[PDB]
Length: 320
Image (cartoon, rainbow, N blue to C red; front, side):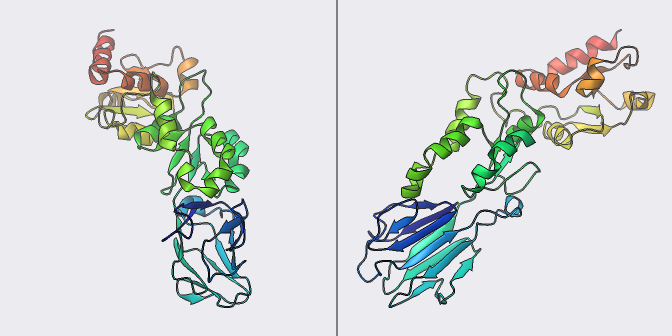
């Protein structure tokens, strides 16, 4: 998100968030979804137009800013950006920091890019929200990215949280939901006028965690909680692999149930099965070894005594 701020009283001490759109900047305009009043003599009545474009697809992966275009409005003294006079056709920038000088005014409008990239749990939710957040200058996606700041969880409020939400939680990603994204649109206009009114994502995250038996006490208490243990897993979900790695598990992967050898059982403490191969399998289960789903493993992780609870179950099965 583009934020603008200025020294002195020229933006009345308020930072502004410039969502994609176009803004006329001068001394004789009124603060609007499309106008920015700058409080200065020696800037023109209508001095400059700032135009913010919607994000590129790349921006979700790069953390790169929306294109910011500056045009001088035929003013007496012109407009500079980062010391460079703006040409008659305007200029556009993808730097993360802009110093904008309007005419003879020595107090510059400073624009800076504040990172916000939102990952979605599933394609359905992304499809609901993508256009809306594009228009807010917030890049969105499903794939993993190093630029991600927030993860939107599926709040089905009727079943276990997804492997994507578990993994985001252990990554120390701020988790948000439906209501935060809706609140964002609701207060859009006041955020343009005062950046400090931007809804706090941490607060939504906190509200989600609190009194929720789907989330452990802390992400930190889960990390390396199961180191020493090894497990075998099927060929699906790399998030599932990454998550079990953050728990400290050494992972083996296997294609078929008939690929559980005497060798594999010997090197494996327990087996992690997919939901389909867990629900329907009867005769083909490996006799000696503990088998469970990610959902079930997560519930053990939620408990205070995860290590023993798993060990107590390893021994429990070792006899039969």
